[PDB]
Image (tube, rainbow, N blue to C red; front, side):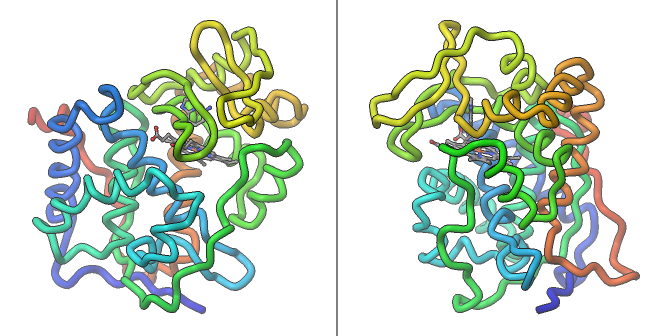
Length: 289
Ligand code: HEM
Ligand SMILES: Nc1cccc2nccn12
């Protein structure tokens, strides 16, 4: 299976900046969502979930096909709550109906990270919608109740190494867990992209507690929470080294996150040699908008 990127006909950087802007403006406008978290965190999670179905072995899944639009994937139990991201993006897709579904979902995540003051994430267009029968089956996204060895093995399927996994998990500073979606609850209301996941892991007093869904999670009295898979990054010595690196170097985290996230969103895609270079979108702030 080769998935060759194909630029939406006649479109260039300025087209995609407009789409970016529309998402960014809606992020600013619809600020009440999820107890004033806003939609930034769920859009990042959406971009990851649409990409994280990829399997390096056969090139199935991945962002290219935009298959989250189909019911099998839309209704994956692992994707519970992402319907809110999809609804957010509906009027954007109405305004810009030429963009492919994969490009929109992935661009949503890029826009969210940047608008939340995260690193710039270079982004390439050209994902092409594929048919319903290309939708990957449920069960390719990771479980949260597991340990470091699970996390490490899981992410080999996505061709991610230890550094990539640890960098990517820093997105867990964002938003919160919701008992009705995942069987985990809490984490506060953060919508600023920082390296605080690593700082919190290292510096908080964590207790292993059961939540109201009868699942174990790690909680601190300050109101922070970590999944078992998050906490595994400080249980495993190789992950721990990396957690400490990012806790001590915000810029390095930003740079590594940006690379890993771009890679995640592009796994499975063949870019022709004469494809445009990745785009780096300006934030609303940078544009004076
Ligand atoms: C072992 C890997 C991972 C596991 C088990 C995991 C699990 C979860 C779970 C259970 C939630 C709560 C969902 C809810 O209840 O609404 C969640 C939220 C989130 N995850 Fe992950 N995740 C993982 C990796 C990632 C990666 C790689 C990213 C992005 C780079 C990501 C970004 C997020 C974001 C942004 C949220 C918050 C969404 C919201 O506030 O609505 N996670 N994650
Ligand atoms: N631990 C965790 C996982 C996913 C999202 C999130 N937000 C705050 C904490 N958190």
